[PDB]
Image: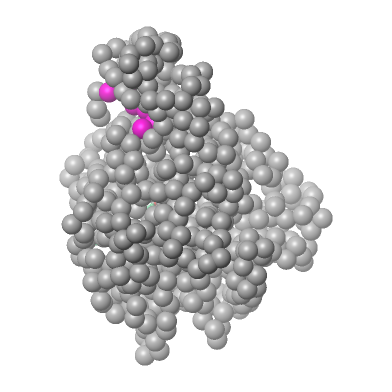
């Protein structure tokens, strides 16, 4: 914990909420000054609990770089029309930096450029059958490509395009690595993952392979193109087949006016996968023998079936699908945004389907539960000193994604008539927290803020002789369970929000992931929209 001002290190929007935090004993006056020193704003800090005081400077609407002074402390804050444009662009460019089997040239990727990796065909587990499944994204700090979390990352990017296309239109991905005519930014980027996902479906059965990885994780020092271990397609799984089905039905709808062929191919692939679900058992995935990579296991598969049924309900607009969706919507499943508990994606597809195709009674019950869920998140946010919908127990592996999915839920609800008054405050507080307004004064994104992430658990950043890591990567965040040797050694006894370390070996607090950047893209695009 530093003895300084805690603020949004990326910046503040002209029209947005503006807040800073300080550990204090009582109210203190504060001032905002031009870089010359002239005061433009003055106020008093106010208590918010657990040693924290806040200062609100929302009314300062003139853009510039300001010196914020409180007691003997000083901080440089930025107010701008589109303060989050650069970070949003970097967060979307992260997906292109994760591209597998693709040359990333220096003119696009700069020092983190590299040649095509993992170009070999993968062997289907326990057979001699080889299969080509190039492309898509390296999942995280490792080089595996896993179906289940890939579906969430795709769904998030598609949702961001559907909700905030104007905000996304102001950002540029690695345009020259993608096929012309160029699609809008979120669709341009997500098409790479959608194309790889299509190669993961078994043509014979419609089932989808759980993942393609090497048998084990290579050293942290491994460059993408030096990872030459043989690739293995882990068996087909119910969770991979269902999440694929839902992500494909969603892409079929979104790509309809942009890529008719992709849309038609996705729609067909979604139907063949749903046919596989009807004929197979809800069997949880477990790593086969000799496969030591990310399992992405899950004992609860009803939420994945809910998402697949609701996604096809919306894709087709066919009331016949509500027969399967509605009993699933009645279950006491958590309504979350993944990677393991995906029911809220299904709830959203159901609520976004024309009203005529569904039971009005079920629809109203669904909308009421969503409102009650948001009220509970709002109460958590009300009692938190940083105003984020989190409790100490929520600071688990990928706590930044836990937070961002919750900000996402408020924003998603606005498109389906559930207008919670706290939605925009939560979105702003989640961005503030991610960018430095937290007990560690840590900006949880590489290459941004005054205290960026400098040592992520990310193979290309470790391997290169740059580190200085790849920019725009959202790290997992504080995890109180101390799920790595570094976290256990350095973070024992520390509060839940301080359970983070910027060290390359801390995979449990300092790794990156495509499905951690994906809700960040959605949340940041929402704020930019205004
Ligand atoms: O780290 C990112 C990727 C890197 N690529 C490989 C891939 O396998 C890895 O994925 C991560 O792999 C991790 C290791 O299994 C998963 O970590 C688990 O993440 C879960 C939440 O998603 C944690 O579960 C929570 O833990 C608490 C008590 O143990 C409970 O209060 C919570 O109920 C529970 O959900 C588990 O402890 C935890 O081990 C992550 O979510 C998942 O993001
Ligand atoms: O840091 C490299 C490995 C160290 N010891 C065993 C492995 O589990 C480590 O690899 C990391 O494991 C985590 C899987 O649990 C994973 O989330 C990271 O992607 C791996 O690099
Ligand atoms: Ca599940
Ligand atoms: Zn690769």
In the displayed orientation, state which residue is furthest to the right.
356
| Magenta region | 4-9
Look at the picture and state if 250 lies above or below 215: above
Percent position (x, y) of residue 30? 37, 12
Task: Please indicate, yes or no, whether residue 419 appears anywhere in the rendered image.
Answer: yes
Percent position (x, y) of residue 471? 33, 49
Looking at the image, which is closer to me, 116 or 321? 116
In the displayed orientation, state which residue is furthest to the bottom.
128
Q: Is 120 left, or right, of 43 in this rendering?
A: left
Look at the picture and state if 428 lies above or below 237: above
Q: Quadrant of residue 42?
A: top left
How many discs appear?
A: 0
Q: Is 138 left, or right, of 243 in this rendering?
A: left
**Residue at screen point 46% across, 30% down:** 80
Looking at the image, which is closer to me, 172 or 50? 172
Q: Main secondary structure of the magenta part?
A: loop
Q: How is the image coloured?
A: one colour
**Residue at screen point 65% across, 70% down:** 260
Percent position (x, y) of residue 112? 29, 58
Percent position (x, y) of residue 98? 37, 61
Q: Is residue 339 magenta?
A: no
Look at the picture and state if 276 lies above or below 473: below
**Residue at screen point 47% across, 52% down:** 172
Task: Please indicate, yes or no, whether residue 68 appears anywhere in the rendered image.
Answer: no
Look at the picture and state if 204 lies above or below 496: below
Q: If the image is split into quadrants, where does the C terminus sit?
A: top right
**Residue at screen point 29% across, 48% down:** 510
Q: If the image is split into quadrants, where does the N terminus sit?
A: top left
């Amino acid at each position: 914990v530093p003895k300084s001002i805690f603020y949004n290190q990326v910046g503040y929007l002209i029209s947005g909420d503006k807040r800073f935090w300080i550990q204090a004993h009582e109210p203190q006056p504060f001032a905002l000054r031009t870089p010359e020193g002239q005061a433009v704003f003055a106020g008093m800090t106010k208590p918010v609990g657990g040693n924290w005081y806040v200062g609100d400077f929302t009314a300062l609407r003139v853009p510039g770089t300001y010196t914020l002074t409180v007691g003997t402390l000083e901080a440089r804050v930025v107010i701008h029309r589109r303060a989050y444009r650069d970070v949003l662009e970097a967060m979307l460019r992260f997906f292109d930096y994760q591209l597998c089997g693709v040359v990333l040239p220096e003119d696009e990727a700069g020092p983190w450029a590299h040649g095509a990796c993992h170009t070999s065909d993968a062997k289907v587990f326990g057979t001699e059958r080889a299969l080509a499944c190039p492309g898509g994204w390296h999942d995280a700090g490792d080089y595996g490509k896993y179906t289940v979390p890939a579906a969430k990352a795709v769904a998030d990017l598609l949702l961001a395009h559907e909700y905030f296309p104007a905000a996304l239109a102001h950002v540029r991905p690695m345009r020259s690595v993608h096929r012309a005519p160029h699609l809008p930014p979120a669709l341009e980027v997500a098409r790479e993952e959608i194309a790889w996902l299509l190669t993961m479906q078994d043509p014979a059965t419609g089932g989808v392979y759980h993942k393609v990885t090497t048998p084990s994780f290579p050293p942290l020092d491994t460059r993408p193109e030096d990872d030459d271990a043989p690739l293995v397609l882990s068996p087909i799984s119910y969770a991979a087949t269902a999440t694929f089905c839902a992500a494909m039905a969603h892409a079929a709808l979104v790509y309809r006016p942009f890529d008719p062929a992709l849309s038609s191919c996705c729609a067909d692939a979604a139907r063949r996968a749903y046919a596989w679900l009807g004929a197979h058992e809800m069997q949880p995935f477990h790593n086969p023998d000799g496969i030591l990579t990310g399992e992405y296991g899950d004992a609860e598969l009803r939420d994945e079936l809910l998402w697949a049924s609701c996604a096809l309900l919306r894709m087709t607009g066919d009331s016949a699908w509500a027969r399967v969706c509605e009993p699933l919507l009645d279950l006491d499943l958590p309504w979350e945004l993944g990677w393991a508990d995906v029911a809220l994606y299904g709830v959203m597809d159901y609520l976004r389907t024309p009203r005529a195709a569904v039971s009005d009674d079920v629809r109203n019950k669904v909308k009421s539960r969503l409102l009650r869920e948001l009220d509970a998140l709002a109460a958590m946010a009300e009692s938190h000193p940083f105003g984020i919908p989190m409790r100490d127990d929520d600071f688990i592996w990928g706590s930044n994604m836990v937070l961002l999915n919750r900000a996402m839920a408020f924003l998603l609800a606005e498109g389906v008539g559930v207008l919670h008054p706290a939605a925009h405050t939560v979105a702003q507080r989640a961005a503030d927290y991610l960018f430095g307004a937290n007990p560690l004064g840590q900006c949880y994104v590489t290459g941004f803020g005054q205290r960026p992430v400098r040592h992520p658990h990310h193979r290309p950043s470790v391997a290169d002789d740059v580190d200085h890591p790849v920019p725009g990567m959202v790290v997992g965040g504080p995890n109180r369970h101390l799920q790595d040797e570094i976290a256990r050694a350095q973070l024992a006894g520390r509060p839940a929000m301080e359970a983070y370390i910027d060290h390359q070996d801390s995979y449990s607090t300092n790794e990156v992931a495509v499905y951690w950047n994906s809700p960040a893209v959605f949340v940041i695009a929402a704020l930019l929209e205004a």
